[PDB]
Image (spheres, coloured by chain):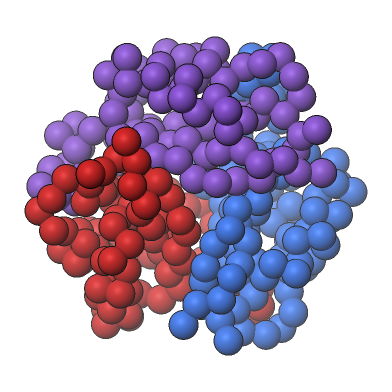
Chain colours: A blue, B purple, C red
Amino acid sequence: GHMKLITAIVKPFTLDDVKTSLEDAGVLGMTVSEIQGYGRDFVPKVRIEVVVDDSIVDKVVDSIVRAARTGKIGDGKVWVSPVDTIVRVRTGERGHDAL
Amino acid sequence: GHMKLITAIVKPFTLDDVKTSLEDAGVLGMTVSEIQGYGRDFVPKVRIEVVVDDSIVDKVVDSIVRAARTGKIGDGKVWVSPVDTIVRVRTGERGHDAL
Amino acid sequence: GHMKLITAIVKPFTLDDVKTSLEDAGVLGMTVSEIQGYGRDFVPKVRIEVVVDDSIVDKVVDSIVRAARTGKIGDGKVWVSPVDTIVRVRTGERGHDAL
């Protein structure tokens, strides 16, 4: 309903900076996956995902963008998509309790 | 329209159990990808995805959660997101025919 | 709003053909990830993602399907899902400027 997935495709060396920015803002539950995207033909990148309430989606996106920017080609993209429902596996908590 | 993507981020050793639970319930077409998430700092996890009709989304989510739960930290998350359209590559079947 | 994510799970040897089809049609920004799906039990596949305006989503899906088809089991799936917002990291461009 109010839940959003943020997907960031960014350079691998920006991971610590993005993670720090998320954790400092109390944004928990990030995952990271390997991915290939255009750069200086493909270069290795990382796919960072978090699920957040829409109240913070704008500032979280901006924080990721700021932390991942180098000003060079291949810096990547950040997009937002709807999440209908979310469940925390361990507890069975749903919605905002699962965040 | 009525189509949903289920994404489950779960511990790698739960894969067979989740797969069995899906296949027993006639939920076909699962994919698996490598992913890293918080656990006992990141631990290896797996990303399991299926596309289903919304008629079964709730019970499929619950079946995955039950199969992947250990009661320990890092058990992961399951979320649902909308799918506008789906096409089976081999046949060009769309919508419910592609499920 | 009008933005869509196309996700294609296809056989790895079709990557060049899909990439060529996308680039020839001026569809930029594709990413590729490793994935496992059903085939001749799992076989290696690739996950190809692009973000496009909904004006071209149908023809882009069809172009990917045509390029990835072999007529054999395991050819994969292509699905479409909504994208609320997108930002190009390097520039901070949003929406259609980030495409």
| Relative height, residue B6 to residue C71 (above, below) | above
User: The C terminus of chain B appears in which quarter of the rendering?
Assistant: top left
| Relative height, residue C25 to residue B93 (above, below) | below
Q: Which of these two is toward me, A93 or C87?
A: A93
Q: How far across and how far down the image is residue A54, in percent?
A: 66, 40
Q: How far across and how far down the image is residue B63, in percent?
A: 46, 14
User: The N terminus of chain B appears in which quarter of the rendering?
Assistant: top left
Is A39 placed left or right of C78 in the picture? right
* Quadrant position of residue C49: bottom left
Residue ID at (51%, 51%):
C84
| Relative height, residue C13 to residue B21 (above, below) | below
Q: How far across and how far down the image is residue C82, in percent?
A: 42, 48
Is C56 placed left or right of C45 in the picture? left
Residue ID at (50%, 28%):
B15
Q: Which residue lies furthest to the right in this view?
A: A24
Residue ID at (72%, 29%):
B74
Q: Does the image show residue A78?
A: no
Residue ID at (45%, 32%):
B6
> How many numbered discs, if any?
0
Q: Does the image show residue C8?
A: yes
* Quadrant position of residue C73: top left
Q: Which of these two is toward me, B57 or B30?
A: B30
Q: How far across and how far down the image is residue A96, in percent?
A: 69, 25
Is A21 placed left or right of A99 in the picture? right
